[PDB]
């Protein structure tokens, strides 16, 4: 899932040297995009959007990825239940 869904930017482990989406590492009592990313440098962290929830279930279930209200163009994925397994994997990795 994560491998092709949401690998391009993100990671989950290791290095986080560069670029992209830094790794989420744990979405179960997180507040915003918070990791050893730098990158939240002008929004989300200041908002402090709590990630331990129900609205997230929907927001992550859909190709939308946003507890804070909004949007879409991660971009025509669609479907089913990729998030379920992903959040499962993060549970096993984190919890
Ligand atoms: C590359 C274009 C991305 C894809 C594909 C997905 N995400 Fe993402 N995400 C991306 C970045 C660069 C960041 C860091 C902050 C920023 O916007 O600069 C994020 C962050 C998140 C977060 C943390 C909360 C936040 O920072 O807003 C979550 C919970 C998240 N992303 C989830 C997520 C999921 C589940 C995706 C597909 C199933 C996904 N993202 C795709 C960049 C990109």
Image: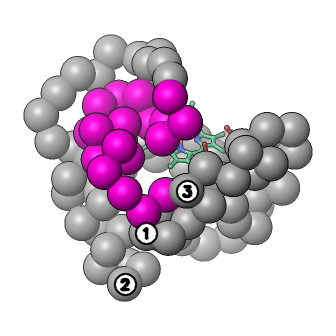
Q: Where, quadrant-wise, is the C terminus in this rendering?
A: bottom left
Q: 72 left or right of 62?
A: right
**Residue 83 among magenta residues:** no
As drawn, which residue projects farthest toward the right?
Answer: 41
Helix, strand or loop status at disc 3: strand
Residue drawn at (61%, 50%) of the image = 49
Above or below — where is 59 with respect to 26? above
Frontmost residue, 57 versus 21: 57
Q: 11 left or right of 45?
A: left
Mark positioned earlier in the residue sequence (3 or 1): 1
Above or below — where is 54 with respect to 31? above
Above or below — where is 44 with respect to 90? above
> Is the residue under label 1 in contact with that under label 3 (CB below 8 Å)?
no
Helix, strand or loop status at disc 1: loop
Q: Which mark is residue 50?
A: 3
Residue drawn at (55%, 36%) of the image = 68
Residue that badge 1 annotates: 28
Frontmost residue, 12 versus 60: 60
Residue 90: x and y in percent read 36, 68
Residue drawn at (30%, 79%) of the image = 92
Helix, strand or loop status at disc 2: loop
The residue range painted magenta reads: 51-69
State yes or no: Cβ of the residue under disc 2 lies below 8 Å from any atom of ligand 1. no
Q: Quadrant of ligand 1?
A: top right
Q: Which mark is residue 95?
A: 2
Crowding around mark 2 (Cα neighbors within 10 Å: few <14, some 14 to 19, many 20+) is: few
């Amino acid at each position: 899932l994560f491998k092709t869904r949401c690998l391009q930017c993100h990671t989950v482990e290791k290095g986080g040297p560069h670029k992209v989406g830094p790794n989420l590492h744990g979405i179960f009592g997180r507040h915003s995009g918070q990791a050893e990313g730098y990158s939240y440098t002008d929004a989300n962290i200041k908002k402090n959007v709590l990630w331990d929830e129900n609205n997230m279930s929907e927001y992550l279930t859909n190709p939308a990825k946003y507890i804070p209200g909004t949007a879409m163009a991660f971009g025509g994925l669609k479907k089913e239940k990729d998030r379920n397994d992903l959040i499962t994997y993060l549970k096993k990795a984190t919890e």
